[PDB]
Amino acid sequence: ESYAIYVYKVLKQVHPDTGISSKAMSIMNSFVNDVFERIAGEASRLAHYNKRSTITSREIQTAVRLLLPGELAKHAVSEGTKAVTKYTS
Amino acid sequence: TRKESYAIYVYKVLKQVHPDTGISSKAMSIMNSFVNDVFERIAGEASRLAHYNKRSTITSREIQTAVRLLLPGELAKHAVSEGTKAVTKYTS
Amino acid sequence: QRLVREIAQDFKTDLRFQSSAVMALQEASEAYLVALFEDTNLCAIHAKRVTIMPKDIQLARRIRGE
Amino acid sequence: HRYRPGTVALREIRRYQKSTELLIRKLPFQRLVREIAQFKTDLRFQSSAVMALQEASEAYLVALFEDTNLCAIHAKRVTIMPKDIQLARRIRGE
Amino acid sequence: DNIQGITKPAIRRLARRGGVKRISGLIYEETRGVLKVFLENVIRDAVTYTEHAKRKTVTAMDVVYALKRQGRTLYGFG
Amino acid sequence: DNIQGITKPAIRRLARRGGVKRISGLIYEETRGVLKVFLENVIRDAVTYTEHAKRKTVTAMDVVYALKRQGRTLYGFG
Amino acid sequence: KTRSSRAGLQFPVGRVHRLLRKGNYAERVGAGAPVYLAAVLEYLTAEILELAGNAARDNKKTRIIPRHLQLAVRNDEELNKLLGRVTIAQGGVLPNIQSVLLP
Amino acid sequence: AKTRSSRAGLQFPVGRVHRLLRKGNYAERVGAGAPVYLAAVLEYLTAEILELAGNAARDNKKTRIIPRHLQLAVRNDEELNKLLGRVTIAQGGVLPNIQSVLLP
DNA sequence: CCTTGGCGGTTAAAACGCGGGGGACAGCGCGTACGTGCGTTTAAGCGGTGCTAGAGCTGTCTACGACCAATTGAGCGGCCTCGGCACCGGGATTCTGA
DNA sequence: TCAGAATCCCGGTGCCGAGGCCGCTCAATTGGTCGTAGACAGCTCTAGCACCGCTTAAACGCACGTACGCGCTGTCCCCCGCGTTTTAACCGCCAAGG
């Protein structure tokens, strides 16, 4: 299993009448996996310096702020905050 | 509160290869950092290897593979030889 | 392909390869050489030369850290 | 009496490659850090933090000047120039 | 000698892609050695991974892991 | 304006340790900017770690981790 | 109902939850981490695909190709910084000629 | 009763390494030989570097080992330089090196 | 605990001027290395046909590690102890420059 | 040659940091129970490797010219070495309270 159908679902929302090749789909799969690994590893590092058992949204946010550039990280944090707010409200 | 270190062990190692030689505190700190860094590197590589083959257990085989990947040249050969000698002596 | 097989014979006799396993090697090698030349051209231009020289290649590798 | 231009330069090169002390003055370096750390207002620092920052900075600058000298020599020049630093930081990947 | 299979016009082609106008006569012999070293390192690491995995076939994922170890991530062959 | 506190003799001494014989009169404004960028990056990372740790005081281990993040790996401070 | 529907996202929260619990990162995970990470991944994916689609429309095409991904990534200030050490297969390079070589 | 270190013939502690592996989120299980092997490797590296440090001290006519001596010992050996090519040592200085074109 | 802050004295240090040698720079004539061009040769890819090494997917079961109680001695620390080494001094030897 | 500025050498002073000895937490060892991980036994089949005829994509030897890499010259832009002046890096004693 992979993220292909979800990538399609994302693509059809920002460009309705377009397609994408399988090689590009594989590249996007690798990109998603790589970013997932980076963020998860950074959060796992952060959770060890403070000797805590649990990785929390705060930990993920700290990893994001450390890993992404300036203008990108602000929007990433905003989107994550909005989602985690809508998850409970 | 008490904290772990490697100083006594490093000193014991030093007293075997140079019977008359002192080591400063700054040097001992550098050695502690070196040991910790190599430990982290080898352990991380081993944990990475353990996941590609879907194994729950990190064994001496994985550790050896990590050391072989991580050390260059004849240093890796000597490291493998020493580790194998010690593991062989441990079982008997 | 022949070159890769020959240089792999030095590490383990009687191996076998995957086509994608060779394709990835080719991609990486071409990218590496293109980057090396991209830096070497800057070296040569800094030397106020058009022609590109092995001393430029060596300087590029030295500064890059290879 | 005068030593010829470059002679004392080599003397300084030798003596400063022999020594191991720090070259930058601590109070100015400290004021610089505590100025550019204003990110989060009203901070506090351990001394060892600044002591480590100075070490890392001087190591980085020495490692940069080594490649600057290499570029200057490759250009068949003695004098280093800012274009050499720019080339070094371009090839280095910055 | 399969290192001679990497042809002079092939290296010229790579330089053209890199943006080089005029090529000296020793660049080819330098590039052959550079490529040989790079490939030797990567192949060594890949074969190490394979021998650890007890395989006889060398997978593409082994090449990808070796390139990641060198620090050159490759997208597409996952 | 404390970046002017990194004096011309200081930069000259650093170049002497680097092995430079003759120094142009324009190296210093470039060196100051490079040092400023490097310090800004490292201090930004350190302050981030501190703010995550819920501390007023910036520790040395924070600086060490910030350098490890960028690939410097300073020894001697724990 | 799916957690993604509650959060209003498109990437699956549950698979991310499983991968966090499976990849040996820590002893515990808080409920918000996978939702946050999925939102981040969805945003990055959408950004990449938006720029790829623009690059694809710029060449009169209807299918995104690795060359288009390469152009989209390398023609952006921050994505290049994020993916500086990544080689894209069948991607190529950016067309540029130094000004001291043109007649 | 005898320690595992004594049973293995090493100087580094097996047990502390065992605990650090089992309390470091590396895997679910840790094999009984892994820490012995790793301690042997670490002891070998420690001895390898200290031999050169002591040689540098004897060369510089000193009884104590200092970070300058460690710097020389590391940078004068090729394999150690390759292994630690991204490590900065505090109070370690640099190597004497003057280019042949700068001096008459 | 130890960081930020304060007053005060010492003197190492940075900044300012100047002489003039070092080398950075524009310009020129010259030699031949590398190019544009072009015939002849090598062998790179196609596709077709075929075999099978070795990757892959079902089942055992016991060797191996996690976990638990009880025992006790190894490692971190506190406190004197003392000598390796810097610091300072008088003097002979090296080396540079005109 | 030979002044004269740097540097190495032998020697005394005395201190502060590398170390031994003594206390005592805690954590390392051993005996023992239990679940299951994964080494092993077994059956299935598909990309890789091999051989062959074929089209033709491509490398390479050779001809020959001008672009450009290079040594050399004149000269003036600027940087080093030294001296003079101003000052804040550094060390010390002391305090509030984060």
Image: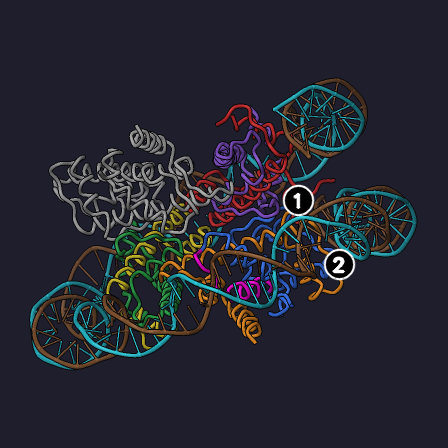
Chain colours: B orange, C yellow, D red, E green, F purple, H blue, I brown, J cyan
Front residue of I89/B71: it is: B71
Where, quadrant-wise, is the C terminus of chain C in this rendering? bottom left
Secondary structure under the numbered disc 2 in the rendered image:
loop
Q: Which residue is mark 1?
A: D12
Residue E45 vs I15, above or below: the answer is: below
Q: Nearer the viewer, mark 1 or mark 2?
A: 2
Q: Is residue E38 above or below residue D6?
A: below
Question: Three-letter amino acid code at disc 2?
Answer: Lys
Tell me residue I16's x, y (percent): 64, 24
Query: Share a chain, discs 1 and 2?
Result: no
Which chain is indicated by disc 1? D
Q: Nearer the viewer, residue H64 or I4?
A: I4
Does the magenta-highlighted stretch encompass residue C61?
no
Q: Judge the density around disc 1: few (<14), some (14-19), many (≥20) Cα neighbours within 10 Å.
A: some
User: Where's residue D3, x and y in %?
Assistant: 70, 43
The circle drawn on residue H31 is none
The residue to which callout 2 is attached is: H61
Q: Residue at x 57, y 74 (%)?
A: B89
Q: Nearer the viewer, residue D40 or D72?
A: D40
In magenta, the rendered stretch is: H27-43
